[PDB]
Image (cartoon, rainbow, N blue to C red):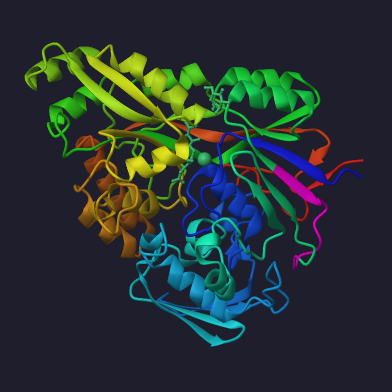
Amino acid sequence: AKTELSMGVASEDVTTLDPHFATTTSDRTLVSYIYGALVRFAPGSANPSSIEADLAESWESNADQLVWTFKLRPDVKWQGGYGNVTADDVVFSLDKARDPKRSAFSGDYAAIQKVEAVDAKTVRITLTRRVPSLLALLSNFSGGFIIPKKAFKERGDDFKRRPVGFGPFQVESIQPGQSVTLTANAEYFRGKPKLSKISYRFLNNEAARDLAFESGELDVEQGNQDQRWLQRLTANPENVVDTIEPAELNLLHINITKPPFNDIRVRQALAHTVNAAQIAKYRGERVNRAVPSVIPSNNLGFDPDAGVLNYDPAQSKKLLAEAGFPNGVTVTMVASQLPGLESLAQLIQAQVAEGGFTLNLQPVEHAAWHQMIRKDLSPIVLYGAARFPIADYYLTQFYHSASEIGKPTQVVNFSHCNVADKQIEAARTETDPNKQIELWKEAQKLIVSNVCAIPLTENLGTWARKNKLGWGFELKGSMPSAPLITEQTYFKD
Ligand SMILES: O=C(O)CC[C@@H](NCC(=O)[C@H](O)[C@H](O)[C@@H](O)CO)C(=O)O
Ligand SMILES: OC[C@H]1O[C@H](O)[C@H](O)[C@@H](O)[C@@H]1O
Ligand SMILES: [Cl-]
């Protein structure tokens, strides 16, 4: 039986395999193969209702939902001889995850007061205030992944390149800018993987990646957001196409503090000459959808009536003239070379010329671009992402003033949005589902009318597999919008 899987992704390299820092789809995908968490999404699901036992066998909460106790499975062992997974490892991981100096996702854990190892198999988490979902924070995504205290202490700066998890796969070696070689974790607590090896290959160029998949060089390849790729790959009977939840929302985040965009009329002019409905139609409706708000449509608290500015390029030119620009505006955007983001920026560039904007694009490799946008190097940021499907996540990270670039608490608030802080904070601890949803909708209307960010389309993850490969479960979703490979993944006879 075939046991070695070859996979091709839209990425140039590994940046970090430390789960408290892994942000790009590619790093998050590799991290989902290496690590586990206290709780997890069911394999093949990106649905929170599927949150179930992983390292924690079970858990208990008190009535005020501030104290959560987790009972750890005793049979879970670390990769690379680091022995049994203990409560001390969980305390270390969660204390690191909630630390802004040692984590990119500390903001998610702001409500945590303390994490205690009651005994070797028992973890107690105490919250200062209520969170919409504590289990969400402790799931196998972002800062929820558990790392060994002793392995991080020993490896330090090398840990991001030599990761240690308790997941079904381990990193044997990294071939910088070429591939990651993963081998089966033979001691994986749910059983020995059916696959012996994963060759995870960096194949950014779409035409080259498609050739490699077509020839059989790859068993799995990442697709794009275009219906032609979808049609061509379905036409060959040896392939199966997977359209994966969650959909990642793409927005033009405008830095509201920088001229000419510190004038609301200029931001409104830009919002009126982008055509999200045309983007969805051009790309294809199965994978792509125009979003009538500034957060993905699958979110608890989503506002379908957020008041998104309509397509009116005549109004754009009228607004620009009122703002002192009768001959238009030139904007230079630092643009990611991730092919989907590059194609999207190219379609935006053609569209915004209708309303008087000359959009110049400075192409930069994706991971380097991620660092530049976090140093305020672009006046506008074309960013595509999904978060845990509760409005608090997307709203805090992208639009709360504490998340703005330049602060030690910075997340992904590229727009320097500061209009919905009170509504975001109030919704976070609001008990009843309806008035919590109303505060979230209030936040969305304020973010939209201030034109902090212009929503475009949201896209489901697109991947192709050869018929011979079975995921070992039905693939509907995966939090990174990329396939999950587990101990159940196998090749058919
Ligand atoms: O989690 C995050 O913060 C980053 C999200 C991660 N997603 C990839 C991405 O932006 C999307 O695929 C994107 O919607 C484009 O391909 C749009 O066509 C990235 O930048 O690699
Ligand atoms: O734009 C085309 C080029 O970009 C791609 O992302 C690859 O890095 C390179 O192999 C290719 O020739
Ligand atoms: Cl990348």
Quarter of the picture containing the C terminus is: top right
Quarter of the picture containing the N terminus is: top right
Residue depicted at x 54% and y 69%:
152
The residue nearer to you, when weighing 12 against 491, is 12
Ligand 2's image quarter is: top right
Q: Is residue 176 left or right of residue 249?
A: right
- What's drawn in magenta, residue-wise? 188-199
Is 194 covered by the magenta stretch?
yes
Residue 151: image location, x then y, percent: 59, 71
Residue depicted at x 42% and y 40%:
368
Q: Main secondary structure of the magenta part?
A: loop
Count numbered badges in the picture: 0
Residue 487: image location, x then y, percent: 76, 56
Residue 163: image location, x then y, percent: 60, 60
Examine the rendered structure and indicate whether residue 190 appears above or below residue 314: below
Q: Is residue 141 left or right of residue 393?
A: right
Is residue 312 something one can see in this rendering?
A: no
Kindly indicate the quadrant of the structure image that contains residue 188. Answer: bottom right
The residue nearer to you, when weighing 208 against 327, is 208
Q: Is residue 179 left or right of residue 198?
A: left
Residue depicted at x 81% and y 50%:
195
